[PDB]
Image (spheres, coloured by chain):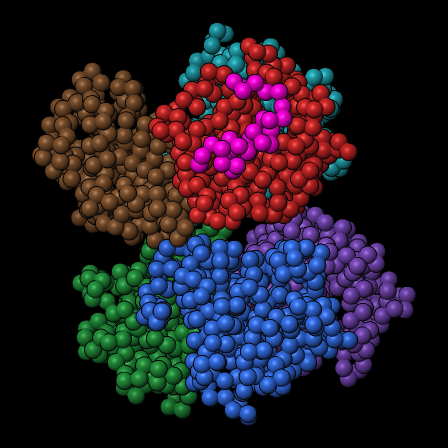
Chain colours: A brown, B cyan, C red, D green, E purple, F blue
Amino acid sequence: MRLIPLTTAEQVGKWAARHIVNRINAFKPTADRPFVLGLPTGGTPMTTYKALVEMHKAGQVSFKHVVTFNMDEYVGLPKEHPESYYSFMHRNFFDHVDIPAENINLLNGNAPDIDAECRQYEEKIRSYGKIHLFMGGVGNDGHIAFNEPASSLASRTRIKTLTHDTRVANSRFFDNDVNQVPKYALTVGVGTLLDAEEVMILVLGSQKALALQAAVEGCVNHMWTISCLQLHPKAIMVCDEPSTMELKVKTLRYFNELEAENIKGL
Amino acid sequence: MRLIPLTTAEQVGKWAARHIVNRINAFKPTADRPFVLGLPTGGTPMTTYKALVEMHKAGQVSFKHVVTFNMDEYVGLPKEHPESYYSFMHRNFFDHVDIPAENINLLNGNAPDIDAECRQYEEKIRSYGKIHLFMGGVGNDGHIAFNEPASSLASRTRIKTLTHDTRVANSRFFDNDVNQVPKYALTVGVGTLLDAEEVMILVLGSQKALALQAAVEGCVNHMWTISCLQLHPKAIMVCDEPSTMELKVKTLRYFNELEAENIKGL
Amino acid sequence: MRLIPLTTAEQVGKWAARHIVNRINAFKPTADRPFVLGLPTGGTPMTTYKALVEMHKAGQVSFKHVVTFNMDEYVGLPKEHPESYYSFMHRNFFDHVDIPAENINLLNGNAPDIDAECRQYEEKIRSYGKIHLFMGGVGNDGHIAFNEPASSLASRTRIKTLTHDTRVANSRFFDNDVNQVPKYALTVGVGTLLDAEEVMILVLGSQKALALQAAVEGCVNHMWTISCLQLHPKAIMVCDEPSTMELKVKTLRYFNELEAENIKGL
Amino acid sequence: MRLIPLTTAEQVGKWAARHIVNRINAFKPTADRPFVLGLPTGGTPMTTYKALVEMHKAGQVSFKHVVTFNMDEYVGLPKEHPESYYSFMHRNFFDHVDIPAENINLLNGNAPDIDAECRQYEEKIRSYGKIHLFMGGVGNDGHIAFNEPASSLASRTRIKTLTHDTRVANSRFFDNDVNQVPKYALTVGVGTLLDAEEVMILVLGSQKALALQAAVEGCVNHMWTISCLQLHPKAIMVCDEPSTMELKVKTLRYFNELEAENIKGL
Amino acid sequence: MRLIPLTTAEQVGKWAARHIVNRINAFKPTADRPFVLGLPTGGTPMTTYKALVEMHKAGQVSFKHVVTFNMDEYVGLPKEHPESYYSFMHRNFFDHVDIPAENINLLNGNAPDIDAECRQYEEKIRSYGKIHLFMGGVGNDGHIAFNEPASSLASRTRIKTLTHDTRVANSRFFDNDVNQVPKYALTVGVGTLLDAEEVMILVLGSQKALALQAAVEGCVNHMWTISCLQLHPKAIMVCDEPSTMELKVKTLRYFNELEAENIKGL
Amino acid sequence: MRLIPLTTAEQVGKWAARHIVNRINAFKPTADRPFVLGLPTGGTPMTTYKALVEMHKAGQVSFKHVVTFNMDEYVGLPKEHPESYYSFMHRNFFDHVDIPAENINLLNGNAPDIDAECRQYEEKIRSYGKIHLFMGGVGNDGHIAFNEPASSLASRTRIKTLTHDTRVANSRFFDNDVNQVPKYALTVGVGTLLDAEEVMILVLGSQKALALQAAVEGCVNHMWTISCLQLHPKAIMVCDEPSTMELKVKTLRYFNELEAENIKGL
C-alpha cells in the first residue's frame, strides 16, 4: 500500500489531481479505449475537484475520452435537490470540464426497481472492462463508499441502509437535521472497488484518524471496510497531517522516507 | 452480512425453514436443474428440521428435485451407530420427506482411502455446479463444519483431527464420555463453503456468544473459521437472544432496525 | 495450516530437507515436467541446505530436473559481493548439487530497468506453470520474503524499500554496519507466494516468536505479511522450541498431538 | 460502579440534580459541618445546573451550608472574561442559588505563584476534611477534569498543558478558533478526585461513547484517566442513550435491570 | 503472584489443604491469637475440604482456635435450605472438624437490616485484626466471591445483584432451573479480600481458562475482578491442567520450573 | 508521567545526570538529612554515570551526604567477581566520586539468610525515611529491577527467579553463555519502588520500544511491571529516539511540545 503523508487538504487535492492527470496522459485514451475514472462526493474530494478543474482550464488534461462512474447516490432524493450526488457532481466538476454527457455514469436513486438498477450499473462497468483508477474518501467509521460496518468484503452494487452515525455525519449538508438525510443509498460494493486497477483514498482531518489506523495498521475485517485495501495490489492513501495522529511513529517514519521525493512538488 | 436477531430457538428454526422454502420455490427446481442444499447436524438445526418437515407435510415444499450434501461425518463410527451423522440425517429429516435416495450425498467416514473419498465428494458437488444454499451451525470455538482452529481459509474437503474441546462438547451425544467421541472427521473445507451461492448459519445459546462476536465484529483469521463469512457475498446469521450478548449495542441496534419487517412473521 | 513443533534448528533442517526430497521423489520430475522449487537465503535455511546437500551426496535426491526460483535479492549490491543472495546460493547449495545452470533463476539486483526485471521474473515462473513448493523464512517483524509491513497481500514481484529494522537485523552479514546493508531489494510478492502449490516456512529462535504468534493466532493483515498463510490451502510452518514461546498452551498442544508420528524420525 | 442508563440529557440532569439534593438533605449541613460539593464546567452539566436551580427555587434545597470546589480553571484568561470557568459558574449556577461567597472555592488561574495556588487549594479541601460528592463530566479521550492522557493516576492539583484535541473540543466556546483556547489550566488531580467520598460522572452524547466504554469495560490505565473510577468505592456514571452505543449488549442489560426501579421515577 | 500448575482437582485439593495446615501450624493459634481463615463454597473447594477433614482426623490439624469467615451467602434463602451456603459449609466441612460454633462467621442472608449485617461483618473482621489466609474460587467470568463484572476494586461487604450468567452457572445446585437461584447475595468486597494477608484461589476446569488468563496475563480491570490479585503482595493460584489452556507457553513454562520442587511432593 | 524524548544515549545521560545534580543541590543534604538515591546497573545507566562523574570532578556535585541503595544483586556470585553488581557499581561510579563507604547500601547476594537480608534492606530504607529519587532502566519485557512478569505490583524486597529471556539478555556480560548468568537475584519490589518520592527510568534502544509502549500507552498489569509507573505521582521516562518507535504519533507529539524548552538546553 502507498501512503502519501502531506500536511494540508490543499496539498492532498493537488497531489491527487496531479496523479489522476499523470495516469490519463500516460494512458493516452481514445474513443475506442477510454480511461475509466471512479469518483466520490463529500467534503473530502473538494480540493481535488478544484485542482483538476484548474489543470483542465490550463490545458493540462482533457476529459473528452474519460468515462466516469460514481460510487454511490441517495435513495429517494430528487435528482435536482442541491445535495443529491448528481447535483454535487455537476456543480463541482462536470459543469466545468469537457467530458461528453454520454461518458457520465451515475446511479439513479429513484429507480423503480433497485435490483435492476444496481445490476445494470455493474454491467455498464463490465462493458468497458475495468475502472482504471477509483478515487474515494473514507467514513469516520471506516466505510468505503456506503459499505457500512458488516458489509461483505466481496459485495457488489446494492442498496444499503445507512448507519445512524453516517446520517448524523452527513446532516452537515442538510442544514444539520438528521431527519432530512436519506436513510438508504445505492452503492458500489467492496468487491466492485477491489476490481478497479488502482484505488486512491483521500483522508482528511482528525475525524478520520481512527479509520486511517484501521486501514493501515488494523486487520482485514468487514466492520471497517476500508481495511479491504490491504487485499488490493495497488492502493494509495493520501493523507493530511491530523489524520495520521493515531498511527505508530515507526509507520509514519517509513512512509515519510519512502515518499520524500514524490511529495516535494513545492 | 445479514444478521437476523430473533429471541428463541423455535423462531430461528421457523425463520430458517421459511427461508429455505422460499429459495426452493423461487428457484423452481427440475430434474435437469436441481436445487442443491448443504446441510449440518448437531443440536443447533433441530428446530429447523422440525419446521421443514411440518411445512413439507403441509404441502409447502417438495424435496423431489433437491440434492443434498452434508457438511461432515465422523471417521471410524459405524454407519448405523445412532449418533453417526448418517443416522442423524435419516432420523431427523430424510425419513420424513420425499427426497429420492439418489439425491442424498453424505461423506463415508469408513472409506478405506480417505483422500479418494474427500476428492470424489468435491467432484460430486462440481458435477452439479454449485451448492445454492449451505446451512450450518457454529462451534463454541468458532469452527464452521469441523474446520477447527488453524484450518486454512482456502481449505477443501479433507480429514481433520478434532480439538479436545469439540470432543468434550460433542460427548453430550455419546452419554457424556469424551473417550467415545471419534477423534477425526471428514469435513468440507472453508473454501468449499465459500463457493456456495448463499450461506446461512444458525447461532443458538450463550455458549456461542463469543463465536458470534468473532464472526460479526472480529477480524478474518483462521482461529475462528466462522470469520470467513466476512469474505462471502451472501451470508446470513440467524440468532437467538442469548447468543448476541457479546455484541456491541450499536451492532445489534443496526441489525434490529434493518430486519424489523423481515422478522415479523408473528 | 500444519505446524511442526520440533526442538532444535538441526531437526528443523532435517525435517525440511526430507519433506523437499519426498515431494521431488513422489513427483518424479522429467525434463519436460520439472519440479519447481522456490528458495530463501538468511540464517534460517542453513541447516536445511546442509541436510539437502548431505542427502544429495548420499544418492537420495537429484536436482537434475528441478528448476529453482529465489525469493529476493539486494538492489545495487555487486553480484560477486560474498553477501549478495547470488553468492549465498552458490556457496551454500548450488556449488554442491547437480542442478543445471540453466535451471537456476535469481533476480538481478543490478538490472538497469527494475520494472522490466520484475515483470520477466513473473513471466519466467508462468512459463513453467507453477512453483510446486516455496520454502521461506520469516522476518522479526513478520515479513515473508521482503514484503515489509504494509505490503499488499495481493502484491507481485517488485522493488521494496527495506525497513530500518530489517537493515539492522541483516547488518550481521555486513560486519555489523547498518550503513553497508542495501536499502532496497527486489522481492516476489505475497500474491506470487500464494500462487505456489505448497509453502513451507522455517521459524527458528526466540526473535521470531512474535512473528509466529502473528502467523498462527493473529488475524490476516498486511503489517505481518506472514499472516497471508492463513489464506493458503497448503502451508506448513516448521518451528524450533524458542519460537513457540508466545503461542497459547492449547495451540501448541493441538499441533503436538497432530504431528507426533510425523516428527518421530529419531 | 453504578451506571444509570437514561435516554435524554434532560433526564440525566434531573436524575443527577435529585441525587445531589438527596445527599445534601440526608447529610443535614450546618455552619460547623458543611456539605462539600465538587463541581464541573462545560456543556455536560447544563441540564443538571438548571434542574438544581429549579429545585432550590421551589424550596427543596438550600446551599447556605454547602461549600463548593470546582475542578479546574484556565490559566491566563481574565476572571471576568465570559468563558472563564469563574464566569461560567456564576452565570449558570451561583447567581441563582443562595450560596455565600465564602463557600465558593475556585482555582485562581491568574495567581502570582501557580505552585502556591495549587497547594493551597489541596489544603483548603483538607481543612474541610473531605469532598462528599464530586460531580464531573468526561472528555472525548477519557480525561476527567483536565487530567489529559498520561496524567498520573495519583496526581494532585497542578498546572497542566492541554492536549490539542481538547483545545479543538473547547474551541466551540471561543467562536471556533483553536488559537483562542488557553493552552494551560489549573486542575485537581486524579488522586484529588479519588479522595472524594462519591464521584458522579455525567456522560452525554455519541462523542463520549468510546470514553464510556473505556471507563466501564476497559482496563485501568492513565491514557483514559476516567478508568480511575474502577478503583473508587462509590462511583456513579449517569448516561444518556447515545453514549452507551459502544458497550456490549450484556453490560447495558445488566445495568438496565439493576436500575429499572431506580429510573422509573420519570 | 505464585501459580501452582498441577494436573488434577485431587492434587489441587491436597496442595491447598497442606498449605492451610502448614500456615496454621506455623502460626500456632491460641484462644487469644486465633488464626483467621476466609472460606468459599461451590464445586471448586470440594477436594480441599475433603483433604482438610482427612488431615484433621489423622491428628495433623486442629481448628479449635481457627476463626472462619465465609465470602458470601444467598439473600432470602432459608438457612436450613440444603443449598444455603450455611448448609453447604456445615455438611462439607464444619460437621467433621472440631471448630467451635463461636468461631464460625457466616453472613446472615435473612437479616432484618441487610445494611447493618454487612457493616457488622466488616467490624467482626476488624475486631480480630486481619484475615491471615483467604481461600476462594473464581467464576467463569472472573468474579471473585460475588463481586460480579463492574464491582469496585475497592468495595466492601454489601448486597449484590447476580449476573444472569452466574445464575445459569449455579442452577446446577437448584436442579438446573435458573428461576430457582437467588438473584441477590451478601458478599465480601474486593477491598475486603485485598486486606487479607494471603489469598489462595483454586482454579479448576476448562470453564475457568479465560478467567485464569485474565488474572495472570490480562490487565487490572473491574470486569474480571480476579485481576485484583495483581495488586496483592501474597497471592497464590493453584490450578489443574485444563484451566491453564489459554495461557502462553512461556507463562506456564516459567511457573512450572519455579514450582517444580514445590509440587514434586506428590 | 513526564516523558523526555531525546535522540541519543549521550543526551539521555546528560539530561538524567543534570536532573540528579539539580535535585541534590536543591535539597542541600547534610550529615543529619542525607539525600537518598536509588541506583541501577546494566548497559542503560552508563552514559549517566559518566556524566555524573564529570560533574562531580568539575566541582558541581558532592556525594559526601548522599546515601545510595541499589535495586538488585545476583545471588551466589562472589562479591569480587567482575560482573557482580557490587563490582559494576564501584568500577563505574563509586570509585570516582567522594561517597563514603558508610553511605553505600547494596544487597548482599551471598548472605547466610537471604530472608533476613531482604527485610533488613527494607528496614534500612525506612530508617532514612524515604528514597528521594530512584533511577532505573527497563527490561525488554518491561521488568523494572528484577520484578519479572507476574511479580506483584505491591511486592517488597525478596529473592526472585529470573526469566530465561532476562538470562539471555544479560549473557552479554557473561561472554554470551546463558549457563553463566545467575538464575536468582535479590531485588527491591515494585512497592519498594513506588514508595520513592520520584522515579526516573532511562529507556535506550529499539529493544526497549515495546516495553516503552507498554509503560506509556498500555494498561497497568503485572506482566509488564514498568506499567506500575502509571500509579506513581512523580515518574519520569527519559528516552532516546529508537525506543519511541512503537508509540503513537500523537503521544510523541504531545511530549515533544511539553518538553521542547526543557530539552533545548542541548
Q: Residue at x 28, y 43 (%)?
A: A261
Question: Which of the two residues, E217 or A61, is positioned nearer the viewer here?
Answer: A61
Residue A51 relative to residue E13: left or right: left
Residue located farthest toward the bottom when viewing the structure as drawn: F32
Q: Residue furthest top?
A: B32
From the top left corner, tell me how far across and down residue C197 is, in percent.
54, 23
Image-quadrant location for residue A43 = top left
Q: Quadrant of residue D144?
A: bottom left
Q: Residue A113: give x, y in percent of width and height.
A: 27, 23
Residue name at image x 64 percent, y 14 percent: C28
Say if the magenta span includes residue B195: no
Q: Position of residue F139 (x, y in %)?
A: 56, 61
Q: Is residue A246 left or right of residue D98?
A: right
Identify the residue at horizontal 54%, vertical 87% (top origin): F64
Taking C235 as reference, is F80 left or right? right
Relative depth, front residue between D163 and B9:
D163
In the rendered view, would you say F259 is above or below B242?
A: below
Residue B14 on image: x %, y %: 50, 30
